[PDB]
Image (cartoon, rainbow over all chains, first blue to last red; front, side, top):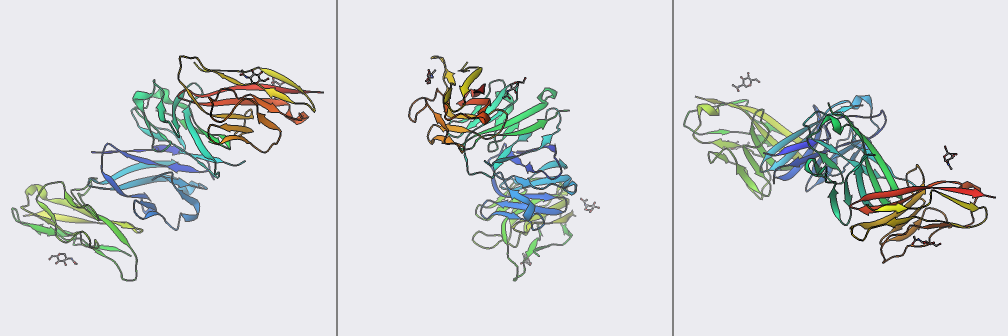
Length: 103
Length: 105
Length: 115
Length: 116
């Protein structure tokens, strides 16, 4: 029904910064909440009402934005791998975008 | 004076793809007058704070504004490869420039 | 921790109705906010059934689905789902998902066995 | 097109003043809007002097620069800049830049050569 664009598959310099970003298009659905997660971890959440929550593991090295996007700071090779933005929306439900990072 | 620019990173995507390009300018209280998205060869688009968006005619069919001051590139082609610049025209600071390198197929 | 309680499987009778039970256990000592309930067929992304905290319910498969517990103006904890007149074509895995802040998503897979 | 006209090189004596002329040539038949004027030492980010269509002129830490030809409330066409009490450190290349819509940026480089 609707489609998620991402920043795609990207590279960055050890110790530098990167923007992770998604857009949900082709649909009127309300965004209730956006989750930024890796396979087994939760980086952050941007809730329409409640705003931003950042996981403790990423708090001191991550910035909210721009928008519903997430900014990774002081990148380490450990930060390499898959990232997901999950849009929780009404009435459509769950949309998912993948971004791959190569630090 | 100070002002840094984070980017969405140097891409490597594939043909027919859609990609988002975005910058963010920080560490400064300076007001943004307008943002220019371009290549050394030509101007892709411009998000001006009062006039809204303008998209260069030979990009109109395959470039969506946003999200934010970013840019969505549609129907990637091998030609789309090259440097890409977001230029913040701001006051009182002046000009900041971020660079994104796209690579297609 | 907020934890979803559901059976791993549920037998139903062809042409009969059945409820897929899905519940969020929230400790008294713990703080949370649930924004919506999402049901989908395992694998698929979207909502067969969705209940939103302000917009209420919205079923998409048809008028053969019902949120038996969820109501507006009341905290969302029970996402239990009723399915009317089941079809051989209804057999499969389903995902009950709770959309919470700040915990994030809590979900389970429930197997629906027809006949 | 909208073309910026200015000299390729300009001379100035130490201890004296000089004007770096920079002007935006716009055909009567074309539509543009100039929102800001920016001078900076060539090749670097940030600025040296800025002129904004509402905020007016700013000078990044100087007391020795002035926009001689540009005012609040009239069309932004002349970026002509004046330096006072020239010094030997002011020898150098400088970018004069017009911020416009829909045309984008128009700039020129100008060599300020300081003499004795």
